[PDB]
Amino acid sequence: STQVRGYDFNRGVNYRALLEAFGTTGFQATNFGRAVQQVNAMIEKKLEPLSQDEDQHADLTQSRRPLTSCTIFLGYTSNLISSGIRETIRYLVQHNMVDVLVTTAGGVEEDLIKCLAPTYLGEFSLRGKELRENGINRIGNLLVPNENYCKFEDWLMPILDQMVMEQNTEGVKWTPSKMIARLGKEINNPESVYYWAQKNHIPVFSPALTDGSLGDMIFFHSYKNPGLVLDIVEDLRLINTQAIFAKCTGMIILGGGVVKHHIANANLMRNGADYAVYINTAQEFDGSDSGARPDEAVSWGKIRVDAQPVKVYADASLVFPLLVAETFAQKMDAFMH
Amino acid sequence: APAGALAAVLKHSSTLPPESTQVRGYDFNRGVNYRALLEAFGTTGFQATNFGRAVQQVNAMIEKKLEPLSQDEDQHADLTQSRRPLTSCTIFLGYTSNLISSGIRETIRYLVQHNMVDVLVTTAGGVEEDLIKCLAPTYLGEFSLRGKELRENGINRIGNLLVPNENYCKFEDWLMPILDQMVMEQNTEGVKWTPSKMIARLGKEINNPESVYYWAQKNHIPVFSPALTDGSLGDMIFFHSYKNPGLVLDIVEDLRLINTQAIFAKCTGMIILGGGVVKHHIANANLMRNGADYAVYINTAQEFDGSDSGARPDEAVSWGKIRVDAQPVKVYADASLVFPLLVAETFAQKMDAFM
Amino acid sequence: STQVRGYDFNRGVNYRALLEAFGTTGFQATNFGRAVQQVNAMIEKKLEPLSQDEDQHADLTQSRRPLTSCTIFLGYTSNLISSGIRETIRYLVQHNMVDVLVTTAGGVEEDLIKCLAPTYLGEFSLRGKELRENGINRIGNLLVPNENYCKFEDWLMPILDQMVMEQNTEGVKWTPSKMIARLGKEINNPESVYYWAQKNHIPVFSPALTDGSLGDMIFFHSYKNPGLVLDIVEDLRLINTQAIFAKCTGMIILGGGVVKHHIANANLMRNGADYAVYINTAQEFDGSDSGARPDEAVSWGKIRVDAQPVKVYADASLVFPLLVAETFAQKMDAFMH
Amino acid sequence: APAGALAAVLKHSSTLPPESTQVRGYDFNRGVNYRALLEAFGTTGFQATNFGRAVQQVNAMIEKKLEPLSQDEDQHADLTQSRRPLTSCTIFLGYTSNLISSGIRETIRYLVQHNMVDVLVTTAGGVEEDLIKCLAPTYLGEFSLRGKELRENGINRIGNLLVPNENYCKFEDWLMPILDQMVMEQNTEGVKWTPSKMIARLGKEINNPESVYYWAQKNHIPVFSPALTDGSLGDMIFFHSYKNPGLVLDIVEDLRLINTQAIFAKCTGMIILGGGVVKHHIANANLMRNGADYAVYINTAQEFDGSDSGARPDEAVSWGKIRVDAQPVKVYADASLVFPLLVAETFAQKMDAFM
């Protein structure tokens, strides 16, 4: 029976002790402490060696990425790539700390665009009329000048030209995940999440990749250079096989919608994830998948019955850097080659 | 009493414009007239007032849609690659999957059955659970039922609703022969499948007037769902492909189809229930015409985490997705409560004109 | 096992059938249907006769109000009196349909002020600077000209004069509930909730009655006419005895904060309410009493273990008129004398 | 590609002012420096950015408070009826009851112990659970624990926290003799009890440096709680009055005490954790000076239902509760996560000046 007790600042500002104290502070501070424990359990599983039998079964993917004792799926909505959590996610991917990424179209394109031009701080209350008259697009309390997307068009159209040519003369069958690997190779910039993902053979799934600026560009491009196909069926096999042949899986899901459901549904194919942390502000009462508690996923078989999943009800821009500080960042040496 | 205090609390006020509307609730001393009760939400305040504003926005869409036009039928079909005739207002209706598991399925089905909207957008669950409900029902439960006991009994939870695993076994038996035919048609009849084309096929096959997608294909209302693999239809396509390889679902052609629905519209309205892809994909299509003319959002998401789901309509104005001169409305509510009321006051009142 | 099925508009717009269909529609529509059932159960208990033994025990209050088989506590936050739900609540109180009211200071004063001047529709986004420069106060998307409070001051100061005089020459010991009955008698207007409450011997509790414009006025008044006392201890005995000697109780609570906790805590004194409906938009995850589910109150003994309470997660301006339409309003003849 | 479509999507943009701040998160290739990590929230966006803005607002309060003044000590005490000396910024700290059950109790206690704020406002639970924690602890649990089983074991739930019934039995034994003395002092020494005066007495009696209210009375920090009867202290006053009748708690005199704290301030700041009375009562006091100079809200309430709890700081500007020229901040978060971080970056950095 653990007693409630908050950090005592009479001790001074001892940051690690202050963070450790969230576990006995209560409400979402305690859920944060539980999330640190769940993620550290994923990491300590991941670093355990594969036995001969485990290695046999897990080798049954055709994937270039070396397999580990715990395959970690990291999912996040577009807004988090607009935010500075882009840097947090880039770090994890750069150091091979996670194994599969799932994001929406915005979460791909805004990473690449930030390599061409920055996003700026604003306010939620800025009025749409005056912004639109000035070509400034609003993302929460962030601002993206539309010139950013004009730079994106310039950068992307030559790649689209090459992709159709490789499709039609070299037999390439494009999928969202194959396109995202190509885009990461092209951006060729170490600040980019997708640069490191393709370098480290970390696949990125985004079944609705046409829902965004990338879609705008493909759409415009298709009038002059018709026939690009993006197949989502092959990518469904690819993500599902990541779960099916894992020794263990963990899910770290930031936000809701397709990124949350698609990771969870893949893990149903192995009868459930072993570890899971949600971080989002959605609420269950309207029945949405976004606001469903981890225990709903247990009824489907998406999380194992014997798992101890946790949801932190909070804006991930506040807690995800703190979570990484207390978990992956303390084990960085183990992830380096 | 301190003089500055008195001056701060008892400050003079300007007179408000003469057309300012007073707050006043429905008076049950009149008895119960449900029409008058709903009309009274407009002057009740808070989200009741936004509901009244949403009635007005949707009634404006409908009245626009009912205006005659003269436009060349053959060129419209050619630029949109669609058999659907243009009207004076193209209405896009988007809804998340949970609402198809709820009884809002019936509400949506009624609108599509009577050809009252022009474009549907939903996620994968919002397709498959309409079809599965023609095979077996969904049941009432509670949000607090524990997942371990449910899982051990083969029962899956959707909010406070429940669906047995066996529903999906029936879905599998129904779907597998259709997937066989789709692969045969792709490989020997040149069909280039996309989600919308598959959803039209599935509605024709289910052949059941309780289904949204049966009515949608009958009435030539396309359904866009660019992540159609993310659910049970996905599971089935996946298992089927190891028995019968080769099905492809392209999303590029469906992007051309939805965007041209917005580009070549005379007017557009957006009615969006929930967040995620369904909200963003409709709004982004409408950026292609420099913005929708009318818009109603009904969802429970909040802006403060920067999510697109929680963004107010005025964020969409900044992008060009809603016109600067539109008067869009968001109702902050569970759509299971307010969408039937909204339909009662709008489309269902205009049923005569839709014949 | 009840199947999900929504209202079919092919039947036409049959309003009562449409409302009845919320119960099988799911999510908060089903919780609304359950709330209709809980409230109708309060009403059908309330109309059951008191047996001789029940009548004996329930007569042990010194209260002028005739006792009934189910004592219904109605609680609501200030914003709902600013809104047109003021009319809904006035109707229930006018026809003796509820037995105890609990509200905050704003929920008293705005009822009285609406008898002097109206509240107007506005928008949530109106900016505070321009409003303040014009003396317009904002309540959500409603607007109250500050002249309304100047009219309140004019109306109220003579009553405060009389109350101190009766305190100091006639032995009157003021409490919030006694002041609210007096204010309702003085406003003498059938549009006012508190007019009907005092006429029908329905007590109104508001332990923090000084937190609002009423407080402002008492404060200003106390410089020229010092010594008014408002005792909250006596009002605590009064509300608790309403629960202790009830045959059955129901709680209908709109909103959170003190109105919710104070009704629930009174009912702990009888080992729990028999029926309960919450309607509010607060969420449980921060640990607040406002966002606690009814099942939290069960652990305290504030709701009986064998009750079937329900929370509707929604803005009460949308659902409370619908709830009243389906419950109290259909039994109006039984409440008339 | 349709020309209007291209023009709508590829619209030119104005250049933003040169001092515009770029978004950029903390880079863990630097390793883990927690100070730099917290500083990085300012440029991370969404509520992380509001957290950084809240650090700045509170640091501005503190810096103002540390400015010297010359003001007549005797007249200030007479107009406020308070022994507390005036400083250059009077800070009001408000917090709902649940936060005293959480470990935020320790955070608040530290601030009051070091005399860093001037006025506390809390609800009844926020008083009594501080005192009870000096008798017996609160435990960690889960939100989903069922009330029937808990009730049958005599365990009471507060969110995901748990407190046994026996905690309140210990409270009863401790409190009853003190209530006896209060009635004796009212009836034969002329004491006119109010909530603040009772809370000062209870803090002196608990005599325990882990208690917020022990430190508050030692440092002459008044605690306002105008519905002090709404909780366990209420239960005890109630049961006690049938054994020893006559205790009165007046709220009118406490209204005079809190309002004069705002009226006679040089500057004020408001730090408000949660909603309800604690938020409204501090803000209303500050209307008496035509508005607070600085304000930080931390709560999870939303505006859309019109509640005062969910109102943004800009609503308070319309009333005169926050000055038109202030730059107030709300962080949309559970205070159990962000208040210790906020204190770490503000008051706890200034500990040297507060000695």
Image: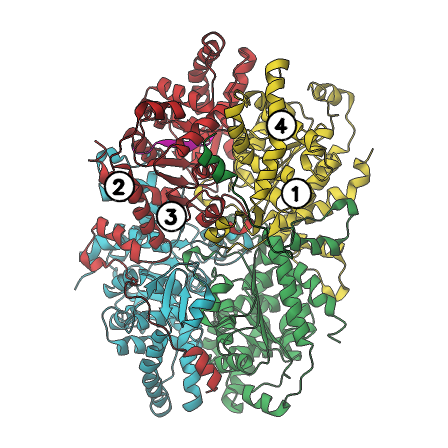
Chain colours: A yellow, B red, C cyan, D green
Q: Position of residue D267 (x, y in %)?
A: 59, 77
Amino acid bearing label 3: Ala
Q: Position of residue A190 (x, y in %)?
A: 74, 37
Q: Which secondary structure lies at badge 3?
A: loop
User: In the rendered structure, the residue with mark 1 lies on which chain?
Assistant: A
Between the residue at mark 1 and the residue at mark 2, the CA separation in whole angstroms equals 45 Å
Closer to viewer: mark 1 or mark 4: 4
The residue wearing badge 3 is B326
The residue wearing badge 4 is A158
Q: Nearer the viewer, residue D305 or A137?
A: A137
Q: Quadrant of residue C141?
A: bottom left
User: In the rendered structure, the residue with mark 4 lies on which chain?
Assistant: A
Look at the picture and state if C51 lies above or below C27.
Answer: below
- Give me the disc on residue A86: 1
- Which residues, given as a range, are shown in magenta? B116-123
Q: Position of residue D283 (x, y in %)?
A: 50, 71
Q: Which secondary structure lies at badge 1?
A: helix
The residue wearing badge 2 is B63
Between the residue at mark 3 and the residue at mark 4, the CA separation in whole angstroms equals 37 Å
Between the residue at mark 2 and the residue at mark 4, the CA separation in whole angstroms equals 45 Å
Between the residue at mark 1 and the residue at mark 4, the CA separation in whole angstroms equals 26 Å
Q: Which secondary structure lies at badge 4?
A: helix
